[PDB]
Amino acid sequence: ASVATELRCQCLQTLQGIHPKNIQSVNVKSPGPHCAQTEVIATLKNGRKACLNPASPIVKKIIEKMLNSDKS
Amino acid sequence: ASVATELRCQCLQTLQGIHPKNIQSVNVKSPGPHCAQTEVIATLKNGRKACLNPASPIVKKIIEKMLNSDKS
Image (cartoon, rainbow over all chains, first blue to last red; front, side, top):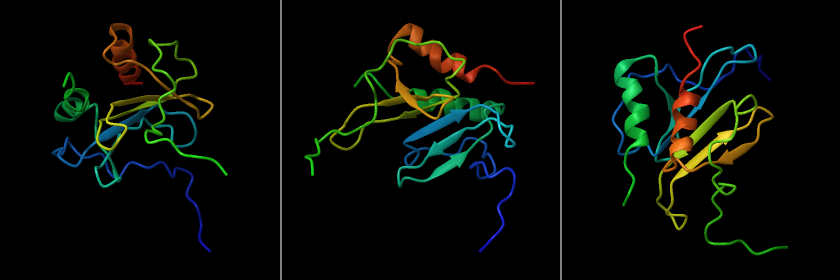
């Protein structure tokens, strides 16, 4: 028994590039429905998720650094 | 009634940067469990998903281009 908002989305409050170690992945979507906003959720190691500001510089790192860590 | 493999994962067969229009987002995960492989799933507009080779050059574009499309 509750009311649903017309946004819903999933971002917490877009953090400014937190530290990884837990951060195992991330998702990036575009606007469309009433959320009409981007999407930038970093799935935490425990299977959680956070949103960050890709427009942010440090956070734009979060994408690139999350992209890094390969060629093992 | 069926048997489960020891990989499961989700990747289709990592495409080499397909065309967007439908592609609305993507997810990028790292190795860990028996899948022990990366993750690069582009969620389709219809709410589907595909995997692509980020090691691939065209596909490394798929990440950057998916990153593009903002500042509206």
